[PDB]
Image 1 (spheres, protein in one colour):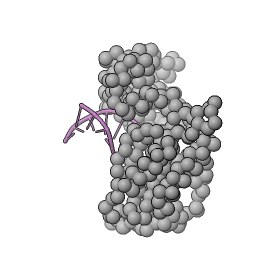
Image 2 (cartoon, chains in turn purple, orange, yellow):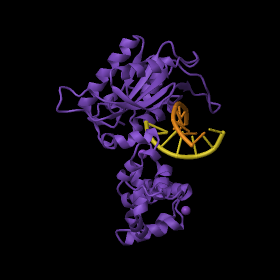
Image 3 (cartoon, rainbow, N blue to C red):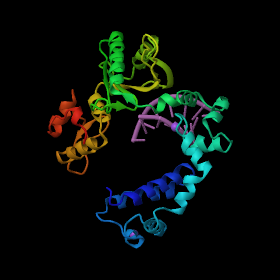
Length: 327
DNA sequence: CATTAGA
DNA sequence: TCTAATG
Ligand code: NA
Ligand code: NA
C-alpha cells in the first residue's frame, strides 16, 4: 500500500505505456499482474532477486526493479516521459471519442494538438467533434450543488412524461459525494422487464423531453436502452452560463433495477465486499440479479427484489445508507 | 462486460 | 462484419 508504492507506480506507468503507445497487450498485461502481486507483498522489496521470487515477475521486471531501487529513477521511464510522440498520444486521448487507436493514427498524421485537432475537425467523427468542442467542460468536476440542480431537473421531466417512470441518479453523487465526474441516471418502467420485449420509445420519450427543454443539448450515443449525451443547466439571468456536462441515461427492466442501482451506486469496494458476503450467505450478486447458491458448485434462480433492502435482507446484512456504501 | 458507432 | 470507445 506504500511499502511498495514506487515499484508499483513505475510498474503501472511502464505498463500503461506499452498499452497506449505501443500496441503490446502482452507486456502490457505483464506489467499489471506484476504490479498486482508486488502490491500485495507484505514487505519492502529490497531487490530484483527478491522481487523475482514472485509470480508474474520475470527477469525483465526484476531488472527494472533494480535500477529503480538503486537510482531514484529509470531510464526507459525517463526516455518515454520525454518523447514527444508518446506524450502526444496520452494527450489526444483526453478527448472524448479519442482513444489509443485514433490517437496513434492522428499523431502519425501530425495532429499532435488541440489546435491541430481543430484545424482538422473534418477528420473527426461526431463523438470526437463534441469531445473537442467541450474539451474544457469535460474535464471539469461536477459540484454536488450543481448535481442537485440537475437531478431536480430530470426527475421533473421523467415524471411529467410518464408517472410510472422510476429514475435514480447513481454514483458518488448518490453516495453523498461533494463533486462528481458525470451524471448517471438509472431508468425504469413497470411495463418493461426481462421478457416484455422492449419498448424503445420507453427511453426515447424522455430523451426527447429532456431535449425539448434544453437540458440535453447533445447526443453522443443514443440506442434503445443506453443514451449517452450532453446536458446543461440553464444559464440564469446572465453573467454566468453553465459548463457543458456528460450524461448517461439507461433503460432498465423493472425486474432488475435495484440490482442495477445497487451496483452502479458502488463504491468499487463496497461492491465486491457486499459481493463477497452473498457467497458466504449462500448467494451470487452481479449487475442484474441475485441467485441462490447451489452446493453442486453452481446454481441459478433469480430471487425477486423490490428495493435495495431485499438484496440486503437476502444476504441478511445491515441496510447501508448509500452515504455509507463507501467500502 | 455490454452497448453503440462506423466504415 | 470488426473494431473502437465509454462506461
Ligand atoms: Na517467479
Ligand atoms: Na478520450
